[PDB]
Image (cartoon, rainbow over all chains, first blue to last red; front, side):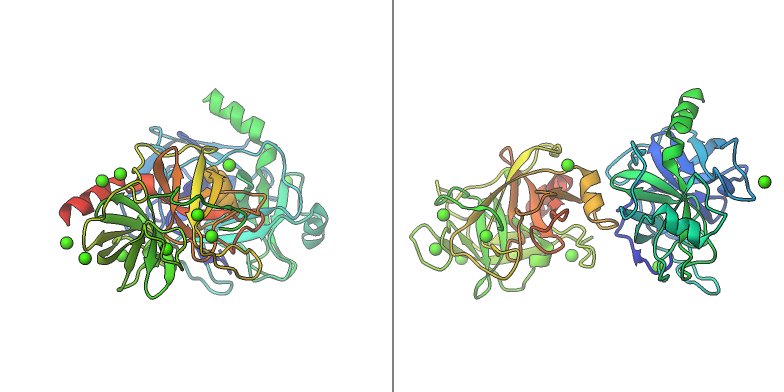
Length: 223
Length: 223
Ligand SMILES: [Ca+2]
Ligand SMILES: [Ca+2]
Ligand SMILES: [Ca+2]
Ligand SMILES: [Ca+2]
Ligand SMILES: [Ca+2]
Ligand SMILES: [Ca+2]
Ligand SMILES: [Ca+2]
Ligand SMILES: [Ca+2]
Ligand SMILES: [Ca+2]
Ligand SMILES: [Ca+2]
Ligand SMILES: [Ca+2]
Ligand SMILES: [Ca+2]
């Protein structure tokens, strides 16, 4: 998160850290056994770390559950990052408590101007490379489809939204990938891509979770 | 209290006024020797005033007992106001009558929608400024964790819940800090913080007392 603030300890209980020795991607807990992330965050063997605030220090609220089944969307294109959504199943159900909780799936898609929470342990810098220990938060609005199409001409598909600022300064960055964009209590976006971080007329593009509620709901029942 | 009503005389017998030359914070009597307040209501010199209705006129039911022990929760953060709870021991035991009584600790956590009574000598305006002589009361519901987080993104932890109105108009304000949120006979909340007072989609944030019952019982027994 570039231009955001340090989240309060466990204020984002649905946020998980995808681990493979170190932190590489983010995700969101939607039930006791299922984490939803990004398809470009796929790798064979992921440890899902829940209840984190400081990813480099053990605090007492962490549940470390390895992935048992990593499912990528079948219609995922990695030329356009279309359908950039991934389902990860845990070994065991995670113990849902006051600081490890689930986020609701969208009952409807979110209008432009609606406010959302983007979170991650990703890069706080826009230039070289710099990673924070504590989770970072970004309050950003959903931009109209028109602004998104004009910011990335011929690039923003059906299954994409832009969330943030045309002025720049505030955006998600490298490492925030797969992370939650939660609007009005519902997971409306997954951190996908953008042109750099916090650039002018270059807001972050996010996966439309509302297009995949049936696919997720079916896949969860399936497996 | 903004948008509340003037409390009946001694209708809130567990309500106390923290004094340090003048009213600044509130508290709740949980036994004859212990007042529970907020950690951000800390001061090295507190006189605990019990049995008050008009804090500016001596009425005859008042017990003025200086604080002997002000104990702040050890894991208290005053950047995020997490663990915003404080225990105050009196010099002398308070004389428990019909106008000075104890409030019960929560036997269980409170559901969303349950109604509660918030009380205080804090500011009655959401606009300018007005501080009352007489205690003020507010009937307000417990909001869902989702609504609280949606109102304060990256700010509401485990140990915080929201009590009030997304519509606005009714809320606690500056000067109500440390005061009781009592639901169905039990102390479920302590007046902590919020973004202004009585603003739209900005309800008051309160310390979740049900998370600290063991800490209170132990701290009181220890000391
Ligand atoms: Ca940690
Ligand atoms: Ca292609
Ligand atoms: Ca840091
Ligand atoms: Ca008042
Ligand atoms: Ca009165
Ligand atoms: Ca007791
Ligand atoms: Ca008086
Ligand atoms: Ca003593
Ligand atoms: Ca402390
Ligand atoms: Ca004394
Ligand atoms: Ca009690
Ligand atoms: Ca609610």
